[PDB]
Length: 49
Length: 103
Image 1 (cartoon, each protein chain N blue to C red):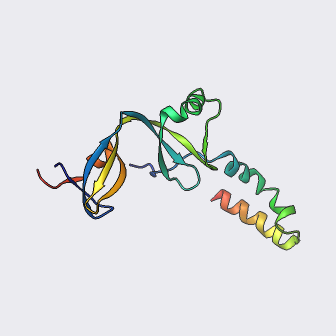
Image 2: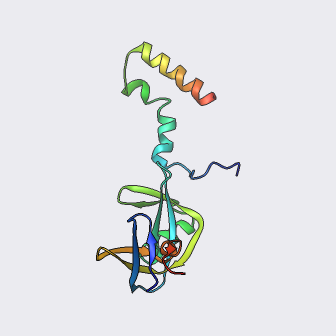
């Protein structure tokens, strides 16, 4: 009962999105360096937390 | 008459037709964490393919689920008539949890 109920290993798509968001976000989503920099920082912070 | 109260339809219900006993497994959705159930005789190939650890994920209708650790049971499909003169399909297991009208 320390386990959170209804949780299951992520699909290979959802899992690849984790190694992709670290790279692919930068060229694809937006090419503005401000948003790129700030988003990479957000990803680092939130992964760490 | 062995009628049971079905909560979802807010009505008493009654068993018209029995199927034979099917082995059934549980499949949990990956994205939402939703839980579904499946005839093992239909998906036998893929299920045994997951039991061999080769392809570990079962796709149905573009929604993909993971097979649960055990969740292998023997259930009977039932056609449950409603007081409206209505028909539902319900598992033995679920119709069993329901509440009797006369006990």
